[PDB]
Length: 127
Image 1: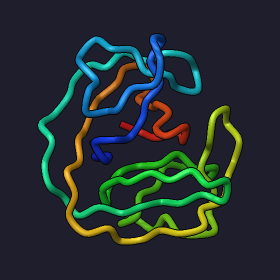
Image 2 (image 1 turned 30 degrees about the vertical axis):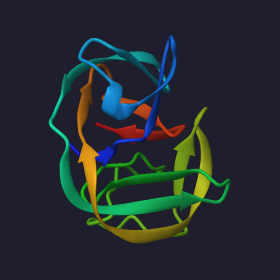
Image 3 (image 1 turned 90 degrees about the vertical axis):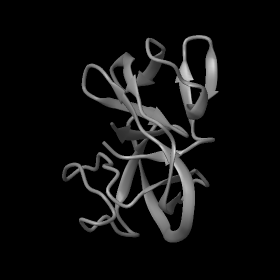
Image 4 (image 1 turned 60 degrees about the vertical axis):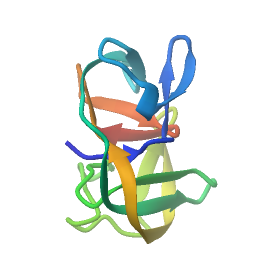
């Protein structure tokens, strides 16, 4: 799937954890409850972007990383823009204020079960 900055926080039953410390078999919170981490991939340096929401939430992801919106999943390469809304916990729409290009950063991909979604920095994201 996509890739997210190493320090991105995901919600486990035992508390928030940085995604670089997530292991296969961990549980991560989604909009439906907890999905299981089915796989992790090696971190790698990738061109990255920062999405900043109107409520101050920020997430750093790859250009093709998919984000649920009210009109369907979208990524930055496929035309996710400032002025559109993402879902924050719990399923509250929040406007994207800025999308900025952040140069090369270490990003990491995890894959989860179920609806393949999980909250990342409290923003609902796709695998």
